[PDB]
Image: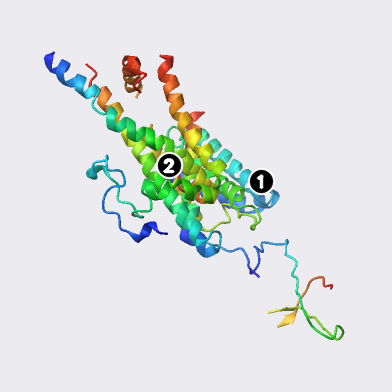
Amino acid sequence: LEVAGLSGPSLEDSVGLFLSAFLLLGLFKAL
Amino acid sequence: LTCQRVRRLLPCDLDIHPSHRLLTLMNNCVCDGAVWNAFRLIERHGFFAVTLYLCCGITLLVVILALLCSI
Amino acid sequence: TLARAAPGEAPPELLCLVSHFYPSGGLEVEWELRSQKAEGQRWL
Amino acid sequence: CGLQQMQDGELTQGSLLSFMIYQESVGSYVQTLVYIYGDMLSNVGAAEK
Amino acid sequence: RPWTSLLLVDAALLWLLQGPLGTLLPQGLPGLWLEGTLRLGGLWGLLKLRGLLGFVGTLLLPLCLATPLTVSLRALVAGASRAPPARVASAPWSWLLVGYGAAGLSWSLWAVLSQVNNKVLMWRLLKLSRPDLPLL
Amino acid sequence: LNSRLSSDTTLMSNWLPLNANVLLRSLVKVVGLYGFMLSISPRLTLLSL
């Protein structure tokens, strides 16, 4: 029985966070 | 992968100066010959998809020509 | 495949397949927690 | 990242190799496009007089 | 000054959202989206009141919506069949550190990224090259 | 003035044969390669950006 814990982000998760932040800041600049 | 059978020592495109080339992780598999094989791509992704993609690529150039002609 | 997250509620239903046994009768299936008596609705 | 996905079972070895080939090719093409466009712009704009 | 204040206010907001405030919020993607919106609203208000939004506002929207948005994209590509995502405040410190790093790196890239003269000169060159259209 | 007329004009048109060819080839190929790598794995395709 797996449970949710304090798992650290994977490398793909870090890349996704970077890309999402980049897109959001670009959108903020756009508007 | 039959592309990895040989080690690529020259740049994939010979019209690019060696100093402007990129040091690729996958030698001889990312060269245009190994990637853009019409028969292999048609077998793997279907005739319609490859034809559509090539048509889109060609229509990009057609659009560039149309823009130049509008002048 | 182990199971999903357990932040509270949403427990998946566990299926136990016993296949190709004779005689049909006399089979006793029991659920345990790892040893303890498992809790949860049970049927066949 | 692709190795992690393959270990997790999301995609097979052949799919990973094909995707790596395609993605490296597009990376090279996009870098070449950007560099050549910038080079043309620099050469045209250096002759401003 | 402004960075320490931002860190303190962010920590306070995350702690508040971890407590009874979070329980009211739903669970899953909507929960993360609402938590991010509340985080952004709190930061925006507490920085507008203290007059420290002159140069730190740009970093607010990414930092607060990088974790939820990311998750959404995953659930849209790899599917939502996996377990419901965890809230930002409840997540360990590594996620917060990676979010800070992502926001900072995106901010630096956008600063570097933010030409008209070159474009007009290139258009002039195209006008001059128009007579050679058949050859092209 | 003569230096402008004999060198800046050369600069303005010094790259068409190579740069134009490279740009057009890359433009033709990128769309198809992106389509293929989307067909294999949209997740890794988004990662590749």
Query: Which kind of residue does numbered mark 1 sit on?
Result: Pro
Chain to which mark 2 belongs: E
Chain to which mark 1 belongs: E
Q: In the image, what residue occupies the spot 38% across and 56% down?
A: B3
Name the quadrant of the C terminus of chain B. Answer: top left
Q: In the image, what residue occupies the spot 20% across and 22% down?
A: F10
When asked about the image quadrant of residue B62, the answer is: top left
Residue E80 is tagged as none
When asked about the image quadrant of residue C43, the answer is: bottom right
Q: Secondary structure at mark 1?
A: helix
Label 1 Cα neighbours within 10 Å, binned few <14 / some 14-19 / many ≥20: few
Label 2 Cα neighbours within 10 Å, binned few <14 / some 14-19 / many ≥20: many
Q: Can you say whether E130 is above or below E72 in the image?
A: above
As rendered, which of E58 and B65 lies closer to the eye? B65
As rendered, which of C19 and E26 lies closer to the eye? C19
> Which residue in the rendered view is the most extreme toward the right?
C25
The residue under label 1 is E30
Q: Position of residue C13 (x, y in %)?
A: 75, 66
Cα distance in 3D space between marks 1 and 2: 25 Å
> Which residue in the rendered view is the most extreme toward the left?
F2
Mark 1 vs mark 2: which is more N-terminal? 1
The residue under label 2 is E106
